[PDB]
Amino acid sequence: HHHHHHMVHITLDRNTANSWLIISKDRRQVRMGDTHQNVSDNKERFSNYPMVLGAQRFSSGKMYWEVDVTQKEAWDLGVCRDSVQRKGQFSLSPENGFWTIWLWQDSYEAGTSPQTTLHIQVPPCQIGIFVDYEAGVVSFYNITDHGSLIYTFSECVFAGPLRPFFNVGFNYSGGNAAPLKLCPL
Ligand SMILES: CC(=O)Nc1cc2c(cc1C)OCO2
């Protein structure tokens, strides 16, 4: 791919974070804490899952960023509508305003309804995410494997401004403590 030149500097929005997340000073890394992180509740925070949004909102153009997933056992990545549900239980699907992929139990899947099996020969340590707003495209790239395509959502109906979307996952196993990190341009 030749999407690198639409690179955008993403930062995480503390106010949207689940109350157990720890966001670094530079707003470029996030991990699961072992307890509540001593913040007040607000209507933006994801209540049920270890999720956080990027601060940036996109309503036009082409955007590209990269995320480090080294040593994680579980995570979700992609984009979502600014108006997605924050409270209670929900699935990740385009009908609910999400365009995502994930790792779970040693398998990679795209967040379609129902979910789609991904075919990845080289487990990724860094994921590239490309959004073309006007074309209605969200694509995922395996940076560890020379940028190979992972998945393309096409005919997307965004229906609003988009935000970068992250889920660090639970750490029930003791093997999923590692952070998600936004990689340098
Ligand atoms: C209905 C359902 O299983 N939802 C869900 C469960 C999760 C999660 C994210 C989502 C969307 O992060 C870890 O546990």
Image: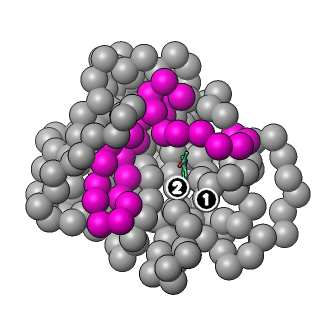
Residue 108 located within the stretch drawn in magenta: yes
The residue singled out by tag 1 in the image is: 50
Range shown magenta = 86-111
Please tell me which residue is depicted at 55% across the width and 24% down the height of the picture: 161
Tag 1, which secondary structure? loop
Please tell me which residue is depicted at 65% across the width and 43% down the height of the picture: 89
The reply to whether the residue tagged 2 has its Cβ within 8 angstroms of ligand 1 is: yes
Tag 2, which secondary structure? strand
- Give the amino acid at mark 1: Pro
The residue singled out by tag 2 in the image is: 167
Is the C-beta separation of discs 1 and 2 under 8 Å?
A: yes
Residue 105 place in picture, x, y as percent = 35, 65
The reply to whether the residue tagged 1 has its Cβ within 8 angstroms of ligand 1 is: yes
Residue at the right extreme? 40
Is 14 rendered above or below residue 180?
above
Please tell me which residue is depicted at 42% across the width and 17% down the height of the picture: 157
Quadrant including the C terminus: bottom left
Q: Depth check: 125 or 57 in front? A: 125
Residue 45 placement, left or right of 75: right
